[PDB]
Image: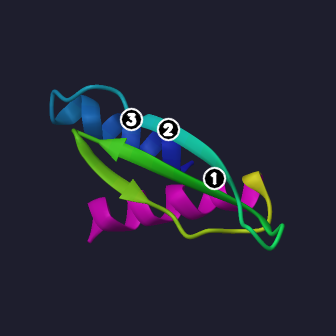
């Protein structure tokens, strides 16, 4: 839903399609965490670090969507 809304926004603004980027992060203490970010119109909205990639994804989606709807 968030990706579709962000895409429709980009189209209305004549901007490039939303760009989703994910990254897996490991610490020196062997702590696995996932982060993601969504670029809208060249403006990057980065989500919070989570335990799973799926949680990281929806986190980035929430951040980007809310920021656009802010």
**Is 45 drawn above or below residue 39 in the view shown?**
below
Callout 3–callout 2 Cβ contact below 8 Å: yes
Image side of residue 13 versus residue 38, left or right: left
Q: Which mark is residue 57?
A: 1
Q: Main secondary structure of the magenta part?
A: helix
The quarter of the displayed image where residue 8 is located: top left
Image side of residue 5 versus residue 10, left or right: right
Say what secondary structure mark 1 lies in. Answer: helix
Crowding at label 3, few (<14), some or many (≥20) Cα neighbours within 10 Å?
Answer: many
Q: What residue do we see at 75% from left, 53% from top?
A: 54
Can you tell which of label 3 and label 2 is closer to the viewer? 2
**Is 46 drawn above or below residue 2 in the view shown?**
below
Q: Position of residue 39 (x, y in %)?
A: 35, 43
Q: Which mark is residue 20?
A: 2
Q: Which residues are magenta?
A: 54-70
Callout 2–callout 1 Cβ contact below 8 Å: yes
Say what secondary structure mark 2 lies in. Answer: strand
Q: Position of residue 29 (x, y in %)?
A: 80, 74
Say what secondary structure mark 3 lies in. Answer: loop
Q: Which mark is residue 18?
A: 3
Please check the rendered image and state whether residue 49 is part of the magenta-colored stretch, yes or no: no
């Amino acid at each position: 839903l968030c990706k579709n809304l962000l895409q429709e926004y980009a189209q209305k603004m004549n901007y490039a399609i939303p760009l989703y980027q994910c990254q897996k992060v490991e610490t020196l203490g062997r702590v696995t965490q996932f982060t993601c970010t969504v670029e809208i119109g060249g403006i990057k909205y980065t989500g919070a670090a989570t335990r799973t990639k799926k949680d990281a994804e929806i986190s980035a989606g929430r951040t980007a969507l809310l920021a656009i709807q802010s």
